[PDB]
Image (cartoon, coloured by chain):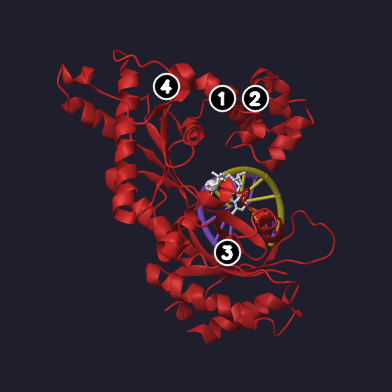
Chain colours: A red, B yellow, C purple
Amino acid sequence: ASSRVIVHVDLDCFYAQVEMISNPELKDKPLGVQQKYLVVTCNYEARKLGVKKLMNVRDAKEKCPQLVLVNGEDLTRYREMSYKVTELLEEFSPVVERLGFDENFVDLTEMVEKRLQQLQSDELSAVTVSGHVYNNQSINLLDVLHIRLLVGSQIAAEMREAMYNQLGLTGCAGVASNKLLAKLVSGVFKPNQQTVLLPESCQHLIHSLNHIKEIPGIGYKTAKCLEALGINSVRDLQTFSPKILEKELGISVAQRIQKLSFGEDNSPVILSGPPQSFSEEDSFKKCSSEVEAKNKIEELLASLLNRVCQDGRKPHTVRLIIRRYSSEKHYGRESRQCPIPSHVIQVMTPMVDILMKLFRNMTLLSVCFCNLK
DNA sequence: AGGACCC
DNA sequence: TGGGTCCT
Ligand SMILES: Nc1ncnc2c1ncn2[C@H]1C[C@H](O)[C@@H](COP(=O)(O)OP(=O)(O)OP(=O)(O)O)O1
Ligand SMILES: [Mg+2]
């Protein structure tokens, strides 16, 4: 083990794609999916007209006074489709990592080897790429690594083909030697296409970023910390002092994101498997009297119970989270965790009050069934 | 419990 | 600004 062939699959405007399959009349027409006062996602037709994801419904219609909107506050169908995609990819190779509802990582390393071993000392020269090659780099058919990434692009092509035939879904794929690069290159040719990255082009891809914040792994926070240090470009981070950085973010985060700035990411593809938790949420115009407004909570449990059930396993912990309006609390949530009565495990009534007492001990309300077994 | 990070 | 995951 040493050289991996990873693939990053990223579905195009996933929610719109599901809504469109539902009611076809929505195709070719600018379609935006709405949650409260936001247009979380939209089909490309609409993006052409200026609709950008996570855009105010207003800023959205006064940019495209024709945009069709559907409500996407209920993630049931999306979720269901998200697992259908993951499963299909699990077929090609079991080790699949989900990143949100629309992303998956697959370690194709073992699969590329098996395929290569079936090729004869001739046909191995007829190996061809499938899709784009980043920075239009030249392929060297004698470079074993090149042969491997190209095979990976074929498999990548196959998965994309299967997704569309079997599930009616289009999307992108990125093939590289680690998760960071694969995710970075999957977006190069945006609408429903695929790109493969050859080693020689790693820095080019890394340096094409305009801000460290663009590097998967570096969030909103870490970015601001780095700024406060005069670290703005990816090369600033590459050339910055190991000591100082290590001494201000933690030898961990430090040593890790600096490897990242170079295109280095040794993290494995974790097998996601079944969810580690189930939760429903609900935001509402500061509309909760601090009581009686727990009929909403009864609502959450309704669906959740239907979900936690279906799964098969049973959760051994419940939780409640809340919010409070006032100033601009850029981060403010509160939750009361608690074990679930063994008897009650094996129905609403009990639970209802269970959350109620958890309620009292304490704009948005959400229940979460975690600790599954 | 709460934090960071991701989509 | 509707869900999730893993670390402190
Ligand atoms: N539901 C969400 N809530 C908050 N932030 C989000 C959400 N989804 C994505 N983001 C963040 C992640 C990134 O910082 C950025 C979005 O990247 P992204 O939306 O995937 O680009 P995109 O043009 O490819 O959209 P899409 O994948 O729908 O086609 O916003
Ligand atoms: Mg996206």
Q: Secondary structure at mark 3?
A: strand
Which amino acid does the dot numbered 3 rest on?
A: Leu
Q: Earlier in the sequence, mark 1 or mark 2?
A: 1
Residue at 68% x, 63% y: name it: A37
The residue under label 4 is A198
The residue under label 3 is A69
Assess whether mark 2 and mark 1 are in contact (beta carbons under 8 angstroms). yes
Looking at the image, residue A204 lies above or below residue A346: above
Q: Would residue A297 appear left or right of A141 to someone viewing this image?
A: right
Residue closer to the observer: A280 or A69: A69
- Tag 1 subunit: A
Which amino acid does the dot numbered 4 rest on?
A: Leu
The residue under label 2 is A234
Which amino acid does the dot numbered 2 rest on?
A: Val
The percent position of residue A279, horizontal first and vertical second, equals 54, 66
Quadrant location of residue A356?
Answer: bottom right
Whole-angstrom CA distance, mark 3 to mark 1, is: 37 Å
Q: Earlier in the sequence, mark 1 or mark 4?
A: 4
